[PDB]
Amino acid sequence: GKAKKKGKSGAARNYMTRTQAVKKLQLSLPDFRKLCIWKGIYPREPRDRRKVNKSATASTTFYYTKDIQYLLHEPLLQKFREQKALEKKISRALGRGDVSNAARLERNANLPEKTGKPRYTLNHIIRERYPTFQDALRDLDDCLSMLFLFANLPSTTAVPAKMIARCERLCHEFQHYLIVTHSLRKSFLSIKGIYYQANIQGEDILWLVPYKFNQRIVGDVDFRIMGTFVEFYMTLLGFVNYRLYTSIGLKYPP
Amino acid sequence: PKNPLLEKRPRNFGIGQDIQPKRNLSRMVKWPEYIRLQRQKKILRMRLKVPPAIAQFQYTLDKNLAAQAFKLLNKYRPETK
Amino acid sequence: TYDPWAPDPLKKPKTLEQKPISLAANGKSVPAVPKPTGGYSYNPAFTDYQQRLMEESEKAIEAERKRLQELELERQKMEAAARSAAEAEAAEARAEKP
Amino acid sequence: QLALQKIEEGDDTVLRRKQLGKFKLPEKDLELVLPDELEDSLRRLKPEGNLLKDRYRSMIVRGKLEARRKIPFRKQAKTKLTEKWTFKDFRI
Amino acid sequence: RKAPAKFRPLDYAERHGYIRGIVKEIIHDPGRGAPLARVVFRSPYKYKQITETFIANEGMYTGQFIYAGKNAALTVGNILPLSSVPEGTVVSNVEEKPGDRGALGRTSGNYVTVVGHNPDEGKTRIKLPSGAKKVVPSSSRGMIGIVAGGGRTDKPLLKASRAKHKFAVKRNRWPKTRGVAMNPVDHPHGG
Amino acid sequence: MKFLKTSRVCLVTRGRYAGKKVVIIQPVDQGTKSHPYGHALVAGIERYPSKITRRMSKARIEKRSKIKPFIKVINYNHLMPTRYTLELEGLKAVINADTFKEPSQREEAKKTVKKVLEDRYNSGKNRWFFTPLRF
Amino acid sequence: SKAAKGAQAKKAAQAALKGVHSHKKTKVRKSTTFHRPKTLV
């Protein structure tokens, strides 16, 4: 029938750049990166990037159009907008001099510096990302390495001190479960740290713990997106610890 | 030592020589009608002769006396909900 | 409490089910925490430590050889450029029925 | 012959030539105790490497995020300073 | 007809210096007895070129550089403000007011003579093709020379077909029936 | 006086290399059997080096400083001589009449011309020869 | 100079009676065209 036009099908429909994804989701760049990390939206590579965008370079990041469509329905977008509006209300109250109203509105913010928990709740995201507890046990390697690393770090704006204490609390609860179930199998002392290998429900779990010294935070890493990873992993480890304690018939939290 | 391959290419912005640079044209921006209306309203109120009953309101308290008045009145704010 | 594992797109896309890109040369998925070898111990076996030392020694040797080679190439390039510049200065000098 | 030439876990140390992000990931720092620095006790151990950098490199290599560089200074908005009308019209 | 025969808008370059344009085409305009000139100028603010349409003066040719502005030379085809020209020169497409891109002396063979200057209030006295005397602002622009195509009306039309072909593109009424040839219901001269 | 001599810089006006700048290696005023007219054997630049800014890296600078040369037999009527000169003894007798009869000799001559021209460009001298003509 | 002394006195009086926030930022606009801002949809 009617002749098709060039660039209206194929890789152009299949991919979009990070700029187009941000403009489509109507988010800021930190919120977009945070949501992509939390929901597991991974960078992709077209066969020819010119067929997607003529101004693309080697540093251009591409994502799936269907992945951005899935991100359009995430309930955390309205949480982000509600928190922005609440911060505007707090600023208005402080500017007018209503300190009691400002404190009452700040109580609704659920700040990590006050609660020790992430600012946004990722309970539905945990179930979306891990369909099975076996998948959770398989990702516990990365989760445990990240949390045992961050349990010994100084307080920052991205990861506050109460959040670090919560990380240490979750790590200690997991260690207590391993002690009471005798699930620990192997240990190793490398030049980098202490490796532990346990066996929880038939899954071999290996993770690395730093030696208790002063850990150096260098500028070659992205510490804020690392903190987003830490928030996701503590949300995972809380549910994992609850399921393990309930399975062995113990009261959680201890 | 600097690279000998580097060169200077000055642009002469005289009449009929080069393309003019992007300058601050904010004095000549075609503003929206509401911005133009409020600015012209302020300008017209300056240009016309104001009767004393309205012109007396342009004489206000200074910063120090306004701050002292607000410092006294902030202890007597009305009851909150 | 809350226990997991016990129009909105309630299903996830196959694009989301696709596996992420691996930067490994062979293309397989890198483990999150790879299993350490005996040569990474703080008090390692003599054979493992010697093997690691020889590998790093030959890597350092070839890296230093490559660095010296490229430094010599840069030196030859700038010497040729200086010789051509002296050539140009000298040239300007004696220029001035079927 | 064309048939024969058509017929003929991941490793962190060796990576593909193409980059994922603004730059290709550099080679890892040397994690090895030199023979002049060996110690006979766990107390005098010298821990090597950076575990935060290791986790960040693991994220980039496994492809959860791309490699980007830090921006220490962002461009400011191009603005012009002008005096307020009340401060212009102040007279004493 | 594609574009109206107008000058460039009065801008900084014409007000303070000059700008050079190149004559690409000299074309016939239907309905007009005078040829038009396509002249391409440079945009001082962007990369793209700007094409204008002037009334061609006699002697202009393709590939010629013309100059428009205050400091432009006194040469046929150059567009100058009337304050920059001496007395006795003839100009074309004279602006009634500075910035209307030309209003006076536009038909073929016609021109406007600069009678005199009054620099005290910046006025210029000019003589129109009808013999009228006018006073214009001295910053009004005019193209030096005489409009090309003069002597067009010296040739008899000689044929109703040639009159018809002339007036069909000019949309003027043709043929013209007389009022005395009409009925009294149609014309006051009817009967 | 004659100006179509050795080390004369000319502009090519016809052919695939039209608009390029060449240096005369050998003027043949009397002509040959293959070319019964006044002609010249020239070496020139097909791809000029790209511009270098102060914030480029060294690898990008050495990538953009490359020069693609060519060698040519060209008629005098297809050359526009310039007042500039480019004297190089590295290009002295780099090509002869028999050079163009074998493809390998043309490649070797082009390699020699590339090396000499890249050295002269890296010297920073004769900037007009390595600047492309805009038309 | 006397003008400099007078200007210093006027600046001090202005700071005493009005404050120190005497200046404001205005945007630099390279174009004379104003566009409607892009808001959340």
Image (spheres, coloured by chain):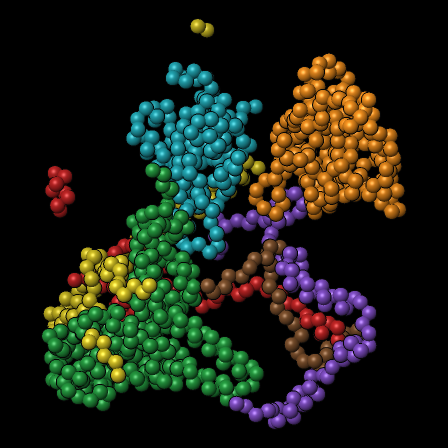
Chain colours: A green, B purple, C yellow, D red, E orange, F cyan, G brown
Residue B62: x and y, percent?
A: 72, 83
**At 17% across and 84% down in the image, what residue appears?**
A246
Residue B46: x and y, percent?
A: 77, 68
Of residue F17 and residue A81, the one placed in the foreground of this image is A81
Of residue F13 and residue B30, the one placed in the foreground of this image is B30
**Quick check: E92 above or below A149?**
above
**At 70% across and 46% down in the image, what residue appears?**
E11
Quarter of the figure that contains the N terminus of chain C: bottom left
Of residue A26 and residue E62, the one placed in the foreground of this image is A26
The quarter holding residue B58 reads bottom right
**At 60% across and 91% down in the image, what residue appears?**
B77
Of residue G38 and residue C18, the one placed in the foreground of this image is G38
Asked if residue D31 shows in the view, the reply is: no
Quarter of the figure that contains the C terminus of chain C: top left
Residue E76: x and y, percent?
A: 74, 30
Q: In this view, does E153 lie to the left or right of A228?
A: right
Residue C58: x and y, percent?
A: 20, 61
The quarter holding residue A130 reads bottom left
Q: Is residue E126 left or right of residue D30?
A: right
Q: Is residue B22 left or right of residue E144?
A: left
**At 13% across and 78% down in the image, what residue appears?**
A200
Q: Extreme top residue here?
A: C98
Asked if residue E123 shows in the view, the reply is: yes
